Amino acid sequence: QVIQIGRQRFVGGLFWQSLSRRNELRAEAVELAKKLKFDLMVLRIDRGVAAAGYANTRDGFAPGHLSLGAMVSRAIALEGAFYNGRRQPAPNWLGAFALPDGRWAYFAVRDHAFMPNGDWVGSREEALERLHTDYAWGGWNVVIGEPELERQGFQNFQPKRLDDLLTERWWALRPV
Ligand SMILES: [K+]
Ligand SMILES: [K+]
Ligand SMILES: [K+]
Ligand SMILES: [K+]
Ligand SMILES: [K+]
Ligand SMILES: [K+]
Ligand SMILES: [K+]
C-alpha cells in the first residue's frame, strides 16, 4: 500500500539487510536479494550505513515507490535528536508517526541502520505494540515520534511529526 505524502508515493515494510562492505556493495545486495527471494531493492550507503531494503512486486511494491524509512532514517542521521536537554546523535532510536491517511509508521534503527523488520506501516494500535516490544530489549537512546507518545512515559522521548523530517534519488525502489 503506497503512502501518499503530498504528491509523492512512499512505501513502508521493506526488509532491511546490512551488507558486509567487503565486496562491490551493489553486487552483494543483488546476490542477497536472490537468496532471500526479493525482486525490488533500495541501497542505503553513507558513512553511517551500508544496507539494502528489499521488497517483492507480488506484495504490491513497485519500482519508483520511495522508501519512507530511507527518508526518515536519513533525516535523523543528519539532525540527531533532542532529549536530556541536549542535541546528540541518535544511532539507536525507535519511533512511531501518524501518516496523512490515518495509518501509522513504525521505525526501529540501531547503529543508524534499520533492524530487519524495523520499517513497518499499519494501525496506530499495532505500531505501539511493536514499539513497546522492541523497547523492552533496551539499548535505545531515545523514542522519536508522534507528540502524543509523551504519555507513554518512555525515559527519553522527542516529539516529532513526519512533516518536520521531510527527495533523494536513492530512495526509489528498483528492479534487482
Ligand atoms: K541485517
Ligand atoms: K536482515
Ligand atoms: K521504507
Ligand atoms: K535478518
Ligand atoms: K530476519
Ligand atoms: K526487527
Ligand atoms: K538491543
Image (spheres, helix red, strand yellow):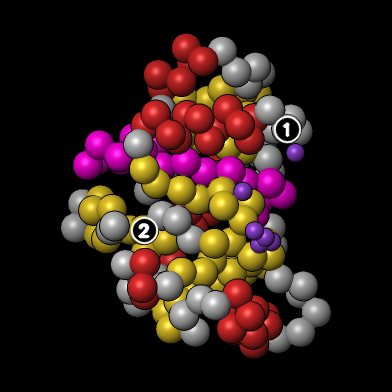
Q: Which residue is mark 1?
A: 137
Q: Is residue 110 left or right of residue 3?
A: right
Residue 21: percent from the left, percent from the top? 76, 74
- Confirm whether residue 145 shows in the render: no
The residue positioned 65% from the left and 17% from the top of the image is: 155
Residue 112: percent from the left, percent from the top? 66, 51
Q: Is residue 23 above or below residue 160?
A: below
Specify whether tag 1 is near ligand 7 (CB below 8 Å): yes
Q: Is residue 4 left or right of residue 95?
A: left
Q: Which residue is mark 2?
A: 11
Mark 1 or 2, which is nearer the eye? 1
What amino acid does circle 1 point to? Trp
Whether label 1 touches label 2, CB < 8 Å: no
N-terminal label among 1 and 2: 2
The residue positioned 58% from the left and 37% from the top of the image is: 94
Specify whether tag 2 is near ligand 3 (CB below 8 Å): yes
Q: CA distance from mark 1 to mark 2?
A: 27 Å
Q: Which residues are magenta?
A: 97-113
The residue positioned 36% from the left and 43% from the top of the image is: 122
The residue positioned 23% from the left and 53% from the top of the image is: 4
Q: Residues within 10 Å of mark 2 (few under 14, many from 20)?
A: many
What amino acid does circle 2 point to? Val
Residue 33: percent from the left, percent from the top? 58, 78
